[PDB]
Amino acid sequence: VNSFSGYLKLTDNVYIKNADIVEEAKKVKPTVVVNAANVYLKHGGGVAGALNKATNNAMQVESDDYIATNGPLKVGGSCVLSGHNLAKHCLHVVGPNVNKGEDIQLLKSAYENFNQHEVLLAPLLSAGIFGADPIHSLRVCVDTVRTNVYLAVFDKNLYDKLVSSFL
Ligand SMILES: O=C(O)Cc1ccc(Cl)c(Cl)c1
Image 1 (cartoon, rainbow, N blue to C red):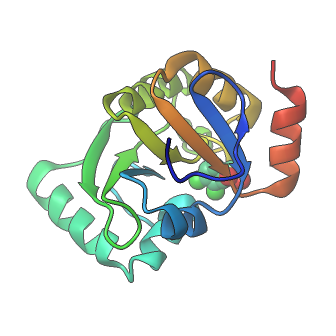
Image 2: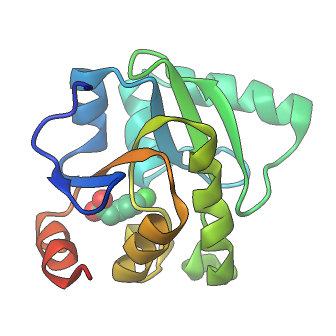
């Protein structure tokens, strides 16, 4: 049993809700919240900007020290940093950004990072401003992630479209 409420069950291990991931994280305080990061951990917009704003920029401060020490992530890669006030940990995962011309084929690699954590609160990788087809992203998620993932979809109309079209 866990603290996630009102999620629709898609598969054995994947659940989905129309929710703001920031508000979800603040309510649940999951062990792991996933950030839809870029390789520089520059948390400007989208989920990253929203999570970082909710940490009062502490996520960005920590991230800048991480990059200064380690250099950028890979597209498809991840790192574990603090969850600050939102979660125990934040798993920063870099899905490909189609609007930057990155290879959509790296989306599966990005979702494989979730398998290192038993339970996660996450957004749909590579959807929204990342420019990928969200139906595709959900399919890759369910076909790749084996651990328990609670997907928080911000856009209402998108949530309805994802559920109605799910195979
Ligand atoms: O939750 C959504 O509505 C879809 C989505 C997923 C990722 C990002 Cl970064 C964004 Cl902006 C939106």
